[PDB]
Amino acid sequence: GPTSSEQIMKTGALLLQGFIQDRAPELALDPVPQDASTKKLSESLKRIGDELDSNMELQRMIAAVDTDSPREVFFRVAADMFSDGNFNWGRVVALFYFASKLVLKALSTKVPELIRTIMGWTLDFLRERLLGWIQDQGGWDGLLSYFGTPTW
Amino acid sequence: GGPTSSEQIMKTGALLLQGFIQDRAGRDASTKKLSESLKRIGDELDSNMELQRMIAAVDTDSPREVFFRVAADMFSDGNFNWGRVVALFYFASKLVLKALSTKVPELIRTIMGWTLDFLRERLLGWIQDQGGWDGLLSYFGTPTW
Ligand SMILES: [Pr+3]
Ligand SMILES: [Pr+3]
Image (cartoon, rainbow over all chains, first blue to last red):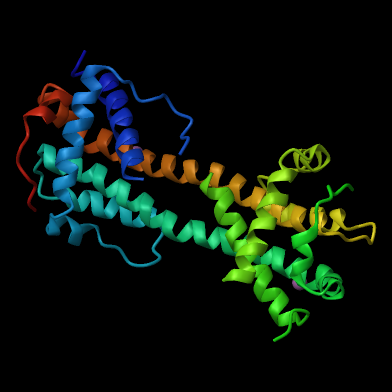
């Protein structure tokens, strides 16, 4: 049934997933259905969502402190969106919009940070194990004439 | 400061490595030429089955526990060549892509989890009363608070 909690939850997840994906990626979930019904809903989501880019009440409500563990932010802000006991479709879509901004925010720190720590380990190993050898070769320009395949 | 100066070598290594990782994640003059040879050797390594096995036999999902051991292992015979130097950059890059392909979907799924959880607690009832999701097609307002 269209009003059964099972269809509402199933559809809501499909809609949320597709909405986050468009605004940002293999989630290994159920794939978003391409039938007409779902398509109509996804397009309605996009139109209301796009309009929320210039909704500054929402931008204010959603603006977070640098580090505060996304979990803290999320529940407080979401309750805040609904704390007067009112509901409408706009606030529901605002909830999806907020989740999407929170993904973006987390990724813009977690990803560079991840790249940095791994590059840190690598350049550190290079400095301590490989540097003298590279010096003895005359620097990095030796790379230009390497055509071998390494074995171990 | 000098092509053989450790300053210049580390500065160049940092740029090459960063650019290398950027290309793999996507899919000056002296430096661009280096970047190109590095891309070539990195591309050749994709079908270096010995390297490929070596990486396969390792738990790439726990990069912290594994990196220095494998790196040390690659040079454990005291020998050096440019291919092995590139293989280290290649390995690093693998760890990065492996982390991205796991942590990014996990991060997104966790946040979707909180959202759907909230929607179920707080909004499920209201949505039911709207007759379900199709109500969305009859909404042309904007929310205020
Ligand atoms: Pr060290
Ligand atoms: Pr709960």
